[PDB]
Image (cartoon, grey):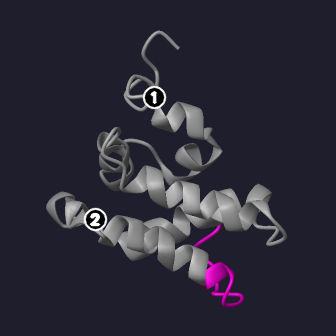
Amino acid sequence: SHMPVPVTCDAVRNKCREMLTAALQTDHDHVAIGADCERLSAQIEECIFRDVGNTDMKYKNRVRSRISNLKDAKNPDLRRNVLCGAITPQQIAVMTSEEMASDELKEIRKAMT
């Protein structure tokens, strides 16, 4: 079974979720693709929350680094794959920041894998 978009919890988790939304809303890219960003953020959020959701240290830093990759000019196609459903919230969350940054690997899913 997969989990639906979760409750706000507290001003930590809801803030992290809305800042991932704001990384998608800072540009009208999601409007051109026709994907609603506010649900997409929460789907990725619950997938990454399983490891990172402990609000002690990594949950604070990982969200900031994630926002950067969602609005980045050196890899602008990364958001394109997520918004169009080419890479699912589950797969992009368990993918490392190194592989997300690589322009080759965000288009290599099952190619020679």
Q: Is residue 9 one of those drawn in magenta? A: yes
Residue 84 in picture, x, y percent from top left? 30, 51
Residue 62 in the image: above or below residue 40: above
Q: Furthest-top residue in view?
A: 112
* Residue positioned 69% across, 68% down in the render: 60
- Left or right of residue 12: residue 108: left
Instruction: Tell me, for residue 32, which label it has, or none.
Output: none
Residue matched to label 1: 102
Could one spot residue 24 in this view of the protein? yes
Residue 62 in picture, x, y percent from top left? 65, 57
The local crowd at label 2, few if under 14, some if 14 to 19, many if 20 or more residues have their Cα within 10 Å, is some
**Magenta residues: mostly which secondary structure?**
loop
Residue matched to label 2: 35
- Left or right of residue 9: residue 90: left
* Residue positioned 71% across, 90% down in the render: 10
Pick the residue in front: 97 or 92. Answer: 97
Q: Amino acid at mark 1?
A: Ser
Pick the residue in front: 43 or 104. Answer: 104
* Residue positioned 62% across, 38% down in the render: 96
Residue 73 in the image: above or below residue 23: above
- Left or right of residue 59: residue 81: left
Q: Amino acid at mark 2?
A: Ala
Q: Is residue 49 one of those drawn in magenta? A: no
Residue 25 in picture, x, y percent from top left? 31, 72
Magenta residues (range): 3-14
Pick the residue in front: 26 or 49. Answer: 26
Residue 75 in the image: above or below residue 68: above
In space, the residues marked 1 and 2 are separated at their CA atoms by 24 Å
Residue 18 in the image: above or below residue 96: below
Q: Earlier in the sequence, mark 1 or mark 2?
A: 2
Residue 110 in picture, x, y percent from top left? 46, 21
